[PDB]
Amino acid sequence: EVRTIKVFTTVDNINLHTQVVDMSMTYGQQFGPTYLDGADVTKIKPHNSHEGKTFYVLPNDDTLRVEAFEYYHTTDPSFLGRYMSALNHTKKWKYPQVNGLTSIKWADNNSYLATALLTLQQIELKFNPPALQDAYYRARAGEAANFCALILAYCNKTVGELGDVRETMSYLFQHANLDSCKRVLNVVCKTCGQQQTTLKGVEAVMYMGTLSYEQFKKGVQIPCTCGKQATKYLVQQESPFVMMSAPPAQYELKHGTFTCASEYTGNYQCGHYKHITSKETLYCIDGALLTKSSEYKGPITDVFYKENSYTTTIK
Amino acid sequence: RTIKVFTTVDNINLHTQVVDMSMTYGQQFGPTYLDGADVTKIKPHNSHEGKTFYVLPNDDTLRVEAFEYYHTTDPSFLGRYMSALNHTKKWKYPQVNGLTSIKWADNNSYLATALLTLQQIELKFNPPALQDAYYRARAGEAANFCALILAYCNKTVGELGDVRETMSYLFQHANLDSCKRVLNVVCKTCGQQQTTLKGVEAVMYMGTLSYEQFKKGVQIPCTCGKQATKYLVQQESPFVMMSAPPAQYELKHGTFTCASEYTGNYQCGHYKHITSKETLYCIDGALLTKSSEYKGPITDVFYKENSYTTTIKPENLYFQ
Ligand SMILES: [Zn+2]
Ligand SMILES: [Zn+2]
């Protein structure tokens, strides 16, 4: 009167849970949304050949919730669904090697993801969630569908939406081990005196307002709260890299003075990112396309620099 | 001879300048504006001494000032803001039913109902520019707020606007972080699937005007081919906005906060605003009409909210 097969369910592909399913009910009626080898089988009834196979499901009990938390480092019950929704699209993208880096061929307004992925491959960073570390290793090998889908899911963005590199890195850095990173700034006003500040973690590696790391060390003019103008400069830096960002204008990149950079062009509300990396010369990676030149000038928005330990000699 | 003036991108940080009356403002500052009017090709006058002029964010410091005030990095923003402001400063902003409206001009009806709506829902803007201008607009000086909405939406004065699109852009610049929405979709073949939305997506819905109908269930396609039922499980927000393609719809006193009526089509049309107070009021630019009931082609309805949790049991969804 009820026929069954044995299957395995999982939210992480590591902890497998035996389930006996009724062959007259769909997987969705028994599990909720269900996937077999990436394929959506929610509307399907079980087949004899499915016996023994592993199905991804969403976490709808305490056991699966704890396992999702330990793998993704999220308590949001919608995370896996939104990740699977992104993954439906990113699994169709192509991820060619371009000058030895995994890129992404243009699809679905994904240029900001391409330059973020290329950047992550050139700065020293360790991700805390096992799912993000695991997917990053796979991305490095040219299978970046899981990693891109996770990026979208951790930024709560959907495929096709406009992405911003600065916001994207900020979300990802929040899931990286940047706790030891340290930054000390000093701000001097001719009338108010000087004020020092110490930043840790993500705030210690990102700055908004200047693209030049060397200008940041020499001092930048910023509005002072007294209404006058003041000079802010970097006193100390402890981090494996720094990310310098600014509202775009026209900026010149020169070989050997930076690690990599992002350029933003086209319609501002739905624009296009290109990646520039410094190797033996400058390479402009534009999705699957490659060009090379001695220098590069354009609307740069983010520049990444290598760092270890810096202390100023100023004052 | 020469005179001292102030340049600015945000009207907070003022940069002292000396200009000469023999050259244009443009030769000295680049593109330059005085209360929205383009004075790039104008020579300074005696009577300009001490006035504050907007300039484009043409070095790193000014680009930081513009970013901190407007929360955009678009280099075209300031020019577009000024171009709109040169017009919106000439609009009239009468008080209608205790609310700041806009007298009709330049196809601005969508901005009027957006402005009237913002004065009736709880919303905090993140950009200082929008915060400051909203407060001024609440008090009746809405020219800068209206010009900023145009700039943020990449719309020019005179262009046909869309209220739903306009609110999307404004909500994008509002603190909606803690807003949350949980939905359930039930298919007889596929079972249940729950979805959670945050931010702008948690307060906006396209497909039905009726908040009550959203709670009770709406029919949608399922990828298996049958129709499924989508309904609201949980809502945490100070308001919700329900939108639909325009259709004849009856608004009843006490059942909604305010709504937008649209007459026209995809190329050209006109919006009016309907608010529920002691009775229903249709604010049509400067014009006020009071009615016990209202019937019209409604496209957006706003409702007050705080915390909602469904009492539907999935197993009973179709007992209706
Ligand atoms: Zn000061
Ligand atoms: Zn179905």
Image (cartoon, coloured by chain):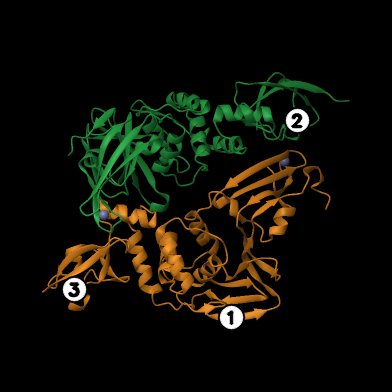
Chain colours: A green, B orange
Would you call the spot at circle 3 few (<14 residues within 10 Å), some (14-19), or many (20 or more)? Answer: many
Residue on which the image places disc 3: B44
Q: Which residue is mark 1?
A: B288
Ligand 1 occupies quarter: bottom left
A35 left or right of A233 in image: right
- Subunit that carries the residue with mark 2: A
Give the image location of residue B73, x and y in percent. Answer: 35, 52
- Distance, label 1 to label 3, CA atoms, is 45 Å
Decide: is B101 above or below A141.
Answer: below
Chain at tag 1:
B
Note whether residue A233 is visible.
yes
Query: Which circle marks residue A45 in the picture?
Result: 2
Please, what is the three-letter code of the amino acid marked with disc 2? Answer: Lys
- Ligand 1: does it lie within 8 Å of the C-beta at label 1? no
Q: Amino acid at mark 3?
A: Pro
Q: Residues within 10 Å of mark 2 (few under 14, many from 20)?
A: some
> Which residue type carries mark 1?
Leu
Q: Are marks 1 and 3 in contact (CB under 8 Å)?
A: no
Report whether residue B266 is seen: no
- Disc 2 vs disc 3: which is toward the camera? 3
Q: What SS does tag 2 mark?
A: loop
Q: Give the letter of the chain under mark 3.
A: B
Circles 1 and 3 on the same chain: yes
**Camera-side mark, 1 or 2:** 1
* Residue in the picture at 43% in, 60% down: B152
Helix, strand or loop at disc 1? strand
Compare marks 1 and 3 and give the one earlier in the sequence. 3
Q: Residues within 10 Å of mark 1 (few under 14, many from 20)?
A: few
Question: Relative to residue B290, is residue A11 depicted above or below?
Answer: above
Q: Quadrant of residue A212?
A: top left
